[PDB]
Image 1 (tube, one colour):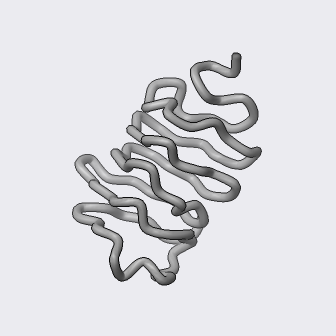
Image 2 (cartoon, one colour):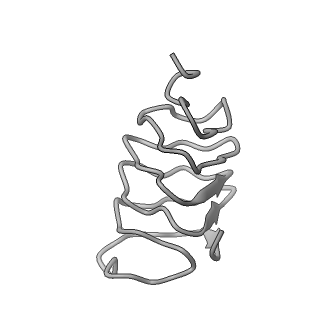
Image 3 (cartoon, rainbow, N blue to C red):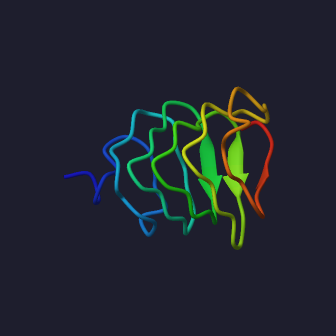
Length: 90
């Protein structure tokens, strides 16, 4: 019972708790769907089940699609669909 799905990190206590957390995540008014954390930072973002956790993710209307790890890095996610998003390391 860690606030919906926050048992170690912070999903903004107001986003989409559709996935537990590891020990390094602080989102703000966002929407994630079965997404992993491990190491990353969110803030005003609407993403779905995505393995992107490295840098900070923000967007008043950002839309991601799965993709892979992040961290201000492109990574092998050329197949990822990101539109209207602002991120850069965490």
